[PDB]
Length: 199
Length: 196
Ligand SMILES: N[C@@H](CCC(=O)N[C@@H](CS)C(=O)NCC(=O)O)C(=O)O
Ligand SMILES: N[C@@H](CCC(=O)N[C@@H](CS)C(=O)NCC(=O)O)C(=O)O
Image (cartoon, rainbow over all chains, first blue to last red; front, side, top):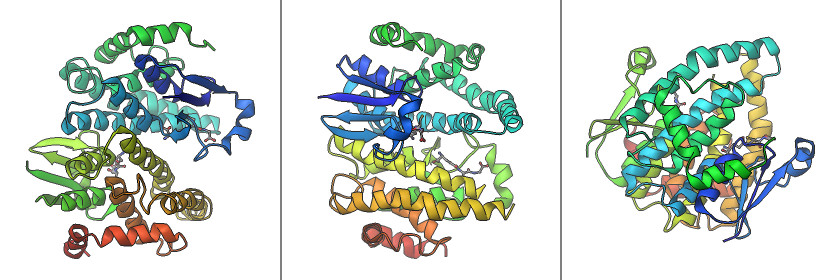
């Protein structure tokens, strides 16, 4: 198939798809958009947002849906419906968490924003990350089913983005950091990290 | 297995799971939580929220994940991974739409303003696209055939209609999809026995 990814010129929600396509070892166009050109491109997307992955000429959006699809293609999904449920539930929970990051990112009042960041760093992150940490510990060192999934790749690629703001944030969570080191050293993901544009 | 669904005593995000369990034709305990008891129950849930579906005692959360799981068990998912992507992408987009709703649900004059953006901007942006998608793709959200996404979509829209009675009336293909789904025998039977 042909693959063309459109996203902004940073990691964000494009990166899970880039990592999955790299893991899949397929060529793909990495179409990156500057923030300056976004009001132009916005009206061209199916629902006004990126990422968009064009597969054999058909535009598909939603980072999670696409990651799962590529995960199936990659052999990084479940062996049965229950195993896929174990992956899906963790990523939907992660996406509930990262909604908090989005609220903080889009706040225009600086003092409120500082208040969101405080709540985020001292209540929200511990609440979710202690559970994620305990879950990974008790699930074989992975998000789900004791084995590598597209969920692990989605989780780590997006957490890496957080490390660009709060650099130490995942360090104290031993099992999150252990999954992080494992994923970024998958050879094709490692390669992508080495060759990817480094803003 | 045994199934126990815990959610509040209204439709909301529990209703897609109730509809899917009904469509699956399996017995389940419909554990409907009153707001008064929610502070007690909240700490017992995996991540502080409902719905929670207990499957032979194991707690699973996340309404979309559960609906997809039950969808696959019910023969209402895709025939291949492309077809499953077609369902999954529409529902994640619908969940983006829903996210705008959730903020309203969370001062009665600032509520009145959030509600004007929802009805006047957010709803028309999304529902025009959903309506035309359904129109030009066989009368369903994905792949020209009934999926768990249709169930999820219509059940949550039905709950939105209990607040904004005319919200889908101008979207004739959405309304038509609604009418198809709620007249499915297993669904219809649920709608008749559920709390008023
Ligand atoms: N649920 C969507 C969220 C996509 C999304 O939020 N895209 C943002 C960038 S991360 C965007 O397009 N912002 C530009 C805008 O909203 O105009 C997904 O997971 O792909
Ligand atoms: N992504 C979750 C969202 C769950 C959610 O937002 N649950 C709300 C009710 S619809 C809740 O439990 N509110 C009570 C609380 O947060 O204390 C899902 O789809 O199940």
